[PDB]
RNA sequence: GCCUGUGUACCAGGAGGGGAACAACCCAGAGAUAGGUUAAGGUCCCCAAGUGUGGAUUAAGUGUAAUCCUCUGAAGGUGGUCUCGAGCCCUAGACAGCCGGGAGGUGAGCUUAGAAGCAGCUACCCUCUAAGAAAAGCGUAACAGCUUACCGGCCGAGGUUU
RNA sequence: CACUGUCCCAACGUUGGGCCCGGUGAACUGUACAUUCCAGUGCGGAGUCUGGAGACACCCAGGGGGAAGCGAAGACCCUAU
RNA sequence: UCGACCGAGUGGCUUGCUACCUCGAUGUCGGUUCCCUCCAUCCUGCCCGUGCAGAAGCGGGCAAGGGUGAGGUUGUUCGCCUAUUAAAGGAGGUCGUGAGCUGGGUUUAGACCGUCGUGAGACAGGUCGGCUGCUAUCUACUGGGUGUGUAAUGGUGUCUGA
RNA sequence: AGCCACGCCACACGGGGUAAGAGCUGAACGCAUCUAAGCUCGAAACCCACUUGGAAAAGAGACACCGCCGAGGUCCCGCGU
C-alpha cells in the first residue's frame, strides 16, 4: 500500500536514511522510522509511506508511522501541551523546576525531595497549583508529563485515602 | 477419586455380562431425561448436541458431574420448569476392575465401577430448545465438556438458520 | 594480534550473517586459503535478541575445573564459530583453523570482499543483533 | 539498639547461671536466650553486658522460681573495652529483672552497674546505687 | 536435617598461592576528578603503637572527646619517579607506547635495573604528543622506586621499582605535570600526594605461613568430641560426594598460606610526620628505631615488619575526609614487656 | 525396559551401508580382487554431494527429533498470523468516532410520608416530530446529574455476523 | 552438687614421627591402553563407545572424590531328589 | 479469601509394582564433617490484589544473591515441645559423604520376659551385652618444583589482559 | 619475643541492561489499547564497578634500557621479610 501525507504550510520535512526530520516555527523533531519493507520518503510537499507488503503486521506499522508524522506536523506548528494539577491534603507540596529536572519537596511530609529529569526540549511551567508541560515532540512531552505524575506514586498505602500528587488534567488532541 | 487415566482407554475387551459379574456398584447418574419429559423433542425449532471427538470410556461419576453441571445451568437460566429438554443418550455398560486388595499374582481386578464407551463422532448429550434459549444450551455444554476426558464439538443439528442469522 | 597476517582473502563481515560467512570461511581454509575476517563487531545474527543473548550467556556461565572457556569479545566469538566448522583436533583441521584470523575493525589497507549469500538487508529486517552488541551484553570491554 | 559506647566480649552463654542483682526475690538466673541475637551452626547463643536476655529463675522464693522473665546484664567477669582503650571487668556476672517496658521489676538494685548500661536502659540506671 | 551454614573461607582470594611479586601491583586506580597528581606512594613497615586522638566525627556523640586508636608506623621517605610511561589505546586494550627517562640516578639503582647510558627523551616525548594528537593516548604513569638505603632498619640497599598512575586534569596538563616531575630526577614525597586524615588503600604481600592445613588456612572445624580421638583431628570429613567423581577446587585443602597480595581499602592516614616521634622505647621489635619521614596508618597493614607497602588514594571511600585530626598523645612505650 | 499367548520376520548364530553412539528400526543377506551404477540415507560447514528451482507459511530458534524406556507434552485457552467459504448492511453514505438533538401530556396509575424512566405491583397509551422508551444502565433520602435506545450533521469505503 | 577443652572455638607449647641426607630394603596389586571433564548412549551405575569441552612434558608434598579401589568363589535370599 | 464434584497434567523426594543390572560382595539406618546443585520461595529485594484508613496481616507475581540458627525427650529419619529469630523453607547429588569419622538402631554367635510350639526352637514382639582391615599404581583436586615451546641474539626491570 | 582470638583494623556507592510490575507514544480495528514497530522506568537477581589469579592467550603479547666477549645468571659465602 501507499499513504500520502501533505506537508502543511510553513513546515519542512527532510528524510536522511531511516530518519525523518520535521521543522516548524515551534521547533524540530527527528524520528527513526524503521520496519521491514516500509519506505518513508519526502516527495515534494508530500511525505510518502509505502510497502509492497499488505499483511496485518505491515498495515499496523504503516498506520503507526502516519500518526507519528502527523503528530510531528502538529508539534512544530501548534505544539503539544499537557495540563497538570498538584493536589495535597495535609502536607503542602513544593513543586519547582530546577535546571533540567522538576523537583518535589515535602511530598507526604518526606524530608527527601523527589526528582525527575525532563525529556528533550520539553518545557515545564508552574503557576501556583497548575503546571503546563509543552514542546514539539509528543514523545518527550507526554513522557515528561507522565514522569511527573508517576513521581508521586505510592505503593504501600491506600491510594483512595492518600491522594496527594501531581496529576495530568488536560491531554492534547490532533 | 482414582484418576480417569486408569479407565479412559478402550484397550480392554467389552465386559458387560451381569450373569457372570457380581458386586457391580450402582450408577451415580440421576436421570437421563431432563427438562420437560411430557413434551416431544420435535416440538422444538432448535436441536443442539455435544459430540465426543475421540473414542473413549467415560465413567458414571464423570457422566453425572457433566450432566449435573449442564442441567444446573439450564435450570438457573431457563428456570426449573423452563421450556426445553436435555437427553443423556449413553448408559455406562462397561464394568471396571481394579487390582487392589499380593502384587501381580492372581491380578484379575475386583469390580470397582462402570463406564460408557463412546465412539468418536457420537452424540453424548442432545438438548432441544427454543431459539431464544439456544446460547444457554451452548453454554451448558461448554461446562459439560470440561468434566469429561475428550475434546468435544458443539453442534446445532436443527434450526441453525434461525440462530443469530 | 597486530602481527600483520598475509591473507589470500579478506572477508568483510559487516552486516553479514555470521554462520553463513563462517561456513564459507571454513571450507576455504580447508582448501588451502589463508583468510582474514574483518569488522567482526559489525557482523550479524538473525532472530530475537533476548533468546540469542540467553544462549551466549549460558555458554559464558557453563564450566567447571576442567573448564569451558567461551569468548565474550566479537573476534573471539566469530573465531569459535569457525572452529565449530573445522575438524580442529585433526592436523589438517588445526592447520586450516590457524590460517584463519578474525579482526575487530579493519587493520588492512584494502576493504574486504562481501561473500555471496551472506549479506543481510537492514531495510528488510528488524530482528537481529550485532556481535558487538552481544559482547557488550556479555560484559566485554568495548575497544571497537 | 543504641550504641553501648563500649566493645563487649560476651562472657555468657545460653544455659549460664548468673546473679540476679535486685530485690525481686529471684536470686539465681539461668540464661535462655538473647534478644535480637542470631548465631551460626554449632555456636552457643552468647550474651554479655548490656544485652537484654530471656531468663529462667533457678534460685529464689517459691513464687519466683520456674518463672520465665526478661532481664538485662549489668555486670560480667569477661572484660569490656572502653573508648580510651582501658578494660573494665567485674567480680561476678549479674542481671536485673525487667518488664516489657524495660523497667526494673524490683525497687532496688544490688551492687554496681556498668555505666554503658545507662546508654541503653534509663530506668535501670536510675535505680542504681553505684555506677562505674 | 543438617542446619545450613556458610562455606569455609572466601573463594575470591584464590588461588591461594605464592605471590609472584613481593612488591604489590595495584589492580585499579582512583578517578581523574582532581588536579594532575601522582596516584600512589610506598614505604616500609616498622611496627605498631597507639595514639590518643580527638574524635572529629561530626556524627559521633563522642565528638571532641579523646579516643585511643591503634596505629601502624610506616617509614615513608621520598621516592624517585625516574620515568614517564605512556599507554596507547588499541583493539586489544592498553599497551605501553614509550617512556621518557631522567638522566639523573640514585647510586643504588643499578642493583635492580640496567640503567640507561643512552636515551633520547625528546624523541619519546614527541612520539607521545603525536599519539595524543591522534587521540590514541590512553594512560600516563610514572616508573618509580624506593630508596631503602634511606631506611637503616631495612637491610636492603636494592630499590623496589613500581609503576604508579598519574591522574587528574586534562590529558595535556597531566602529561606536562608528569614530565616536570621526572626531569628533576623525580624526587617526591608522601606530603605531595597525601594529607593526614585522608583515606588510602594499602596494598602489601602478607606474612608467609608456608604450608598450612584447612583448619588454619580455610577456617574449617577441628574434629569434635569422640571423633577427635579416633586418629583424625585436623582433617575434613570428606573430599566430596560420590558424584561428581572428582575433587572440586572449592573443597578446602592444605597448601601455601600467607605471602599473598592483599589490597586493604579505606585506611585512614592519622599523621604524616618526620623524626622520632612515633618510635618505641627499645626499638620496634625485629625492626629498629624510626627517625625520619613516616606515616601513621589507622589499625593494621598487610605484611611483616620491613615489607614494602604501597599507598593509593581510596578508590571507594565510605566517608568524607576529615583533615588533620588532632593527636594528643603517641605512645613510645616499649613493645617488649 | 511388566507377566502370559499367538502369526510372522529378525537378533541369538547376520557381515557391510544408514541411524551421533546402539542385538533385533531402514537398506542389505556376504568367496577374493578390480571398474562401474544404485539402495537406505543424504547434498551450508564439520562431511562425499545444492548455500538447487518454482511457490507459500512460520518469528515461536517454533523447528532443524521416521520408529523409540530413549524423540513428551494434555484438558483448556488464543483480535498472533495466513487461507477458503456463508449471511446481512453500505455512496439513497454503511461500521466507528466527534458535534448537535434525545421533546410535550407527565412527576403515567397504583403503592407510598414522598415513589419524579429507573424500591414494588399493573399498564405501557398519546401528541409534536427528522427523531426520542409510561426508560436499557449507572446515580439520588427523594428530585439533580451522567449516559443507552432513537434522529440529524461532519467524514467517506468498506463494515458486520458466522 | 562438685569438676572439667566433651562443647562454644579454637590457640600455643613438649616428646616421637613426618620432610632432606648416608646405609639397609620388602609387600599388596597389575587383560591391555590410559592427561581427563560435561552430557549422551550402552545388560538400565563408562578414563576407553558418541558428541562436545579441556589438555605442553616430567617431578615433590598432601588429604583420600572416582577407578561401582584392594582384600574374601555372599554370611542374607533362593535353588540342589 | 476458602473452595467440593469431575476433568487434564507435571515431578521422581514416599509407598507399591516389575525382576532389567550386581550374589568369584557396588559395606546398613541415623548422625556427623565437607563440597556443589534444584525451585514448587520460609526470610530478605522489587511488585499486584485485598473483605487495602493506619499499624499488623492475608493472598498472589518476579526472583535461588545471601540467610534459614540454639536447645529438652527419642538410635531415630520423622515428629513433639521451649526460648530466641528477618526467617528459623523444602529437595537432589549411589535415600551425596564408613580406602573420612561414629556405631545408638536393624541383623551373627550369650541371656531374660511375653506369646506360640509335645519339642528342637520360633516371633518381627520387647530387653541387657556384643569387632569397624589396606604402606595409593592410575585418575581428581589443593599447593610446591624442574624442563621444553614462544625464540637463526641474549638479558634486566616494568606492564598489558584473553 | 613470637605465634595466636576471646583482641584490633578494613570489607560500597553509583552506573548500565532486564524480570514481575507501573507507564508513554501508537496502530492493526478513524475509537480504545503499556505492544504489534518505537520509548520512559523498574528486583538483594544479570553486567560493569572493587579484590584475587593470569604470557602456554600456539594470534604463545607490549615498553624502556643493557648486552652479543660479554649484559646478565647459576654455584659459593653471611643471612631471613
Ligand atoms: Cl570454566
Ligand atoms: Cl577434530
Ligand atoms: Cl524482521
Ligand atoms: Cl536461644
Ligand atoms: Cl567431627
Ligand atoms: Cl572511607
Ligand atoms: Cl542368507
Ligand atoms: Cl539458537
Ligand atoms: Cl556423631
Ligand atoms: K549381590
Ligand atoms: Mg499497611
Ligand atoms: Mg550441632
Ligand atoms: Mg575408632
Ligand atoms: Mg609486646
Ligand atoms: Mg603492659
Ligand atoms: Mg546363543
Ligand atoms: Mg563437500
Ligand atoms: Mg526447541
Ligand atoms: Mg512419535
Ligand atoms: Mg541409558
Ligand atoms: Mg572425546
Ligand atoms: Mg558364591
Ligand atoms: Mg540361613
Ligand atoms: Mg566401593
Ligand atoms: Mg518461581
Ligand atoms: Mg546459589
Ligand atoms: Mg547414602
Ligand atoms: Mg545430604
Ligand atoms: Mg567413601
Ligand atoms: Mg571402613
Ligand atoms: Mg585406610
Ligand atoms: Mg550397636
Ligand atoms: Mg542399646
Ligand atoms: Mg543393643
Ligand atoms: Na500370595
Ligand atoms: Na474435555
Ligand atoms: Na540465527
Ligand atoms: Na564458560
Ligand atoms: Na586410627
Ligand atoms: Na588416637
Ligand atoms: Na562410598
Ligand atoms: Na537370520
Ligand atoms: Na552406525
Ligand atoms: Na532450537
Ligand atoms: Na587439651
Ligand atoms: Na581416592
Ligand atoms: Na519406585
Ligand atoms: Na561381582
Ligand atoms: Na550415614
Ligand atoms: Na535465594
Ligand atoms: Na529433637
Ligand atoms: Na551406594
Ligand atoms: Na554411616
Ligand atoms: Na568403618
Ligand atoms: Na540500575
Ligand atoms: Na611467552
Image (cartoon, coloured by chain):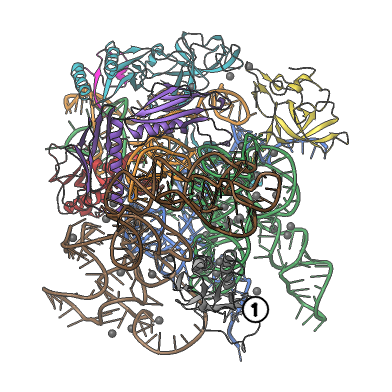
Chain colours: A purple, C red, D yellow, E cyan, F brown, G blue, H green, I orange
Residue assigned mark 1? B25
Q: Nearer the viewer, residue F146 or E72?
A: F146
Look at the image and tell me in which quarter the N terminus of chain B lies: bottom right
Q: To which quarter of the image does residue E165 belong?
A: top left
Q: To which quarter of the image does residue D66 belong?
A: top right
Q: Residue furthest right?
A: D62
> Quick check: which quadrant has ligand 4?
top right
Residue B45 visible in the shown view: yes
Q: Left or right of B84: which side holds C82?
A: left
E108 falls in the magenta region: yes
Q: Is residue A110 above or below residue C114?
A: above
Q: Which residues are magenta?
A: E93-117
Q: To which quarter of the image does residue G7 belong?
A: top right
Query: In x, y percent, where is residue B139?
Result: 51, 65
Q: Left or right of D116: which side holds E313?
A: left
Query: In x, y percent, where is residue E303?
Result: 47, 25
Q: Nearer the viewer, residue F21 or A55?
A: A55
The chain under label 1 reads B
Q: Nearer the viewer, residue A38 or G21?
A: A38
Density class for disc 1 (Cα within 10 Å; few <14, some 14-19, many ≥20) is few
**Label 1: element kind:** loop
Q: Left or right of B61: which side holds E195?
A: left
Q: Nearer the viewer, residue I35 or B48?
A: B48
Residue C69 visible in the shown view: no
Look at the image and tell me in which quarter the C terminus of chain B lies: bottom left
Amino acid at each position: 500500500p501507499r499513504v500520502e501525507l501533505e506537508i502543511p504550510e510553513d513546515v519542512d520535512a527532510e528524510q536522511d536514511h531511516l530518519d525523518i526530520t520535521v521543522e516548524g516555527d515551534n521547533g524540530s523533531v527527528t524520528r527513526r522510522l524503521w520496519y521491514p519493507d516500509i519506505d518513508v520518503s519526502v516527495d515534494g510537499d508530500t511525505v510518502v509511506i509505502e510497502s509492497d507488503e499488505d499483511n496485518a503486521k505491515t498495515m499496523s506499522t504503516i498506520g503507526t508511522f502516519q500518526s507519528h508524522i502527523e503528530n510531528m506536523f502538529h508539534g512544530v506548528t501548534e505544539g503539544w501541551e499537557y495540563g497538570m494539577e498538584v493536589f495535597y491534603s495535609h502536607f503542602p507540596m513544593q513543586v519547582n523546576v530546577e535546571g533540567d529536572e522538576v523537583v518535589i519537596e515535602n511530598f507526604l511530609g518526606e524530608k527527601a525531595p523527589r526528582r525527575t529529569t525532563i525529556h528533550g526540549d520539553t518545557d515545564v511551567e508552574i503557576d501556583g497549583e497548575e503546571l503546563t508541560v509543552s514542546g514539539p515532540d509528543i514523545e518527550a512531552v507526554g513522557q515528561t508529563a507522565a514522569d511527573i505524575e508517576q513521581l508521586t506514586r505510592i505503593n504501600d498505602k491506600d491510594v483512595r485515602v492518600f491522594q496527594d500528587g501531581v496529576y495530568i488534567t488536560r491531554k492534547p488532541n490532533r | 477419586d482414582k484418576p480417569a487415566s486408569m479407565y479412559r482407554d478402550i484397550d480392554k475387551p467389552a465386559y458387560t455380562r451381569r450373569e457372570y459379574i457380581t458386586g457391580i456398584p450402582g450408577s451415580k447418574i440421576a436421570q437421563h431425561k431432563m427438562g420437560r419429559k411430557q413434551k416431544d423433542a420435535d416440538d422444538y425449532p432448535v436441536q443442539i448436541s455435544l459430540i465426543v471427538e475421540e473414542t473413549v470410556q467415560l465413567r458414571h461419576g464423570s457422566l453425572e458431574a457433566s450432566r449435573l453441571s449442564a442441567n444446573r445451568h439450564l435450570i438457573k437460566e431457563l428456570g426449573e420448569e423452563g421450556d426445553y429438554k436435555m437427553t443423556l443418550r449413553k448408559f455406562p455398560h462397561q464394568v471396571l476392575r481394579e487390582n487392589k486388595q499380593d502384587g501381580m499374582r492372581a491380578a484379575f481386578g475386583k469390580i470397582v465401577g462402570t463406564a460408557a464407551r463412546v465412539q468418536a463422532g457420537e452424540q453424548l448429550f442432545t438438548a432441544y430448545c427454543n431459539v431464544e434459549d439456544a446460547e444457554h444450551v451452548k453454554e451448558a455444554f461448554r461446562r459439560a465438556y470440561n468434566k469429561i476426558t475428550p475434546s468435544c464439538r458443539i453442534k446445532v443439528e436443527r434450526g441453525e438458520e434461525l440462530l443469530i442469522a | 594480534s597486530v602481527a600483520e597476517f598475509d591473507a589470500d582473502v579478506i572477508v568483510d563481515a559487516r552486516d553479514c550473517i555470521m554462520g553463513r560467512v563462517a561456513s564459507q570461511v571454513a571450507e576455504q581454509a580447508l582448501d588451502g586459503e589463508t583468510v582474514a575476517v574483518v569488522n567482526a563487531e559489525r557482523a550479524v545474527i538473525t532472530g530475537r535478541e533476548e533468546q540469542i543473548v540467553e544462549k551466549y550467556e549460558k555458554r559464558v556461565d557453563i564450566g567447571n575445573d576442567n573448564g569451558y572457556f567461551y569468548p565474550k569479545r566479537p573476534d573471539g566469538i566469530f573465531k569459535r564459530t569457525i572452529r565449530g566448522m573445522l575438524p580442529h583436533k585433526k592436523q589438517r583441521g588445526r592447520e586450516a583453523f590457524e590460517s584463519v584470523r578474525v579482526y575487530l575493525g579493519n587493520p588492512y589497507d584494502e576493504d574486504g570482499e562481501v561473500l555471496d549469500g551472506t549479506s543481510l538487508d537492514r531495510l528488510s529486517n528488524i530482528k537481529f543483533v550485532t556481535l558487538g552488541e552481544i559482547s557488550e551484553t556479555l560484559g566485554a570491554n568495548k575497544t571497537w | 539498639m543504641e550504641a553501648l559506647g563500649a566493645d563487649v566480649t560476651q562472657g555468657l552463654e545460653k544455659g549460664s547461671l548468673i546473679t540476679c542483682a535486685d530485690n525481686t526475690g529471684a536470686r539465681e538466673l539461668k540464661v535462655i536466650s538473647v534478644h535480637g541475637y542470631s548465631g551460626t551452626k554449632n555456636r552457643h547463643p552468647k550474651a554479655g553486658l548490656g544485652d537484654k536476655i530471656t531468663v529462667s529463675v533457678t534460685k529464689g522464693t517459691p513464687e519466683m522460681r520456674r518463672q520465665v522473665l526478661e532481664a538485662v546484664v549489668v555486670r560480667q567477669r569477661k572484660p569490656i573495652r572502653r573508648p580510651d582503650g582501658t578494660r573494665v571487668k567485674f567480680e561476678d556476672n549479674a542481671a536485673v529483672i525487667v518488664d516489657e517496658n524495660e523497667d526494673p521489676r524490683g525497687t532496688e538494685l544490688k551492687g554496681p552497674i556498668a555505666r554503658e548500661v545507662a546508654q541503653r536502659f534509663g530506668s535501670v540506671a536510675s535505680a542504681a546505687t553505684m555506677i562505674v | 536435617p543438617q542446619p545450613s551454614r556458610p562455606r569455609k573461607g572466601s573463594l575470591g582470594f584464590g588461588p591461594r598461592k605464592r605471590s609472584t611479586s613481593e612488591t604489590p601491583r595495584f589492580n585499579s586506580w582512583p578517578s581523574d576528578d582532581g588536579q594532575p597528581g601522582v596516584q600512589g606512594f610506598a614505604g616500609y613497615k616498622a611496627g605498631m603503637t597507639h595514639v590518643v586522638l580527638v574524635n572529629d566525627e561530626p556524627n559521633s556523640p563522642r565528638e571532641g572527646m579523646e579516643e585511643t586508636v591503634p596505629v601502624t608506623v610506616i617509614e615513608t621517605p621520598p621516592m624517585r619517579a625516574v620515568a614517564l610511561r605512556a599507554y596507547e589505546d588499541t583493539p586489544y586494550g592498553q599497551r605501553p607506547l614509550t617512556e621518557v627517562w631522567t638522566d639523573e640516578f640514585h647510586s643504588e639503582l643499578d642493583r635492580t635495573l640496567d640503567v640507561p647510558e643512552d636515551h633520547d627523551p625528546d624523541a619519546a616525548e614527541e612520539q607521545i604528543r603525536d599519539a595524543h594528537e591522534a587521540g590514541d593516548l590512553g594512560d600516563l604513569r610514572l616508573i618509580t622506586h624506593t630508596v631503602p638505603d634511606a631506611v637503616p632498619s631495612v637491610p636492603k640497599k636494592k630499590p623496589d621499582v613500581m609503576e604508579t598512575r598519574v591522574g587528574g586534569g586534562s590529558v595535556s596538563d597531566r602529561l606536562d605535570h608528569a614530565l616536570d616531575i621526572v626531569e628533576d630526577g623525580g624526587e617526591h614525597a608522601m606530603n605531595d600526594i597525601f594529607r593526614a586524615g585522608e583515606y588510602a588503600d594499602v596494598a602489601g604481600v602478607t606474612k608467609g605461613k608456608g604450608t598450612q592445613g584447612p583448619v588454619k588456612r580455610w577456617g574449617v572445624q577441628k574434629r569434635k568430641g569422640k571423633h577427635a580421638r579416633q586418629g583424625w583431628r585436623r582433617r575434613i570429613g570428606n573430599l566430596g560426594p560420590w558424584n561428581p567423581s572428582r575433587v572440586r577446587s572449592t573443597v578446602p585443602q592444605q597448601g601455601q598460606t600467607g605471602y599473598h597480595q592483599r589490597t586493604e581499602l579505606n585506611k585512614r592516614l592519622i599523621d604524616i610526620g618526620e623524626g622520632d616521634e612515633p618510635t618505641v622505647d627499645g626499638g620496634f621489635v625485629n625492626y629498629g628505631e624510626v627517625d625520619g619521614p613516616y606515616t601513621l596508618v589507622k589499625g593494621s597493614v598487610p605484611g611483616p615488619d620491613k615489607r614494602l607497602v604501597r599507598f593509593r588514594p581510596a578508590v571507594r571511600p565510605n566517608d568524607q575526609p576529615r583533615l588533620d585530626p588532632e593527636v594528643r598523645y603517641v605512645s613510645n612505650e616499649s613493645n617488649q614487656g
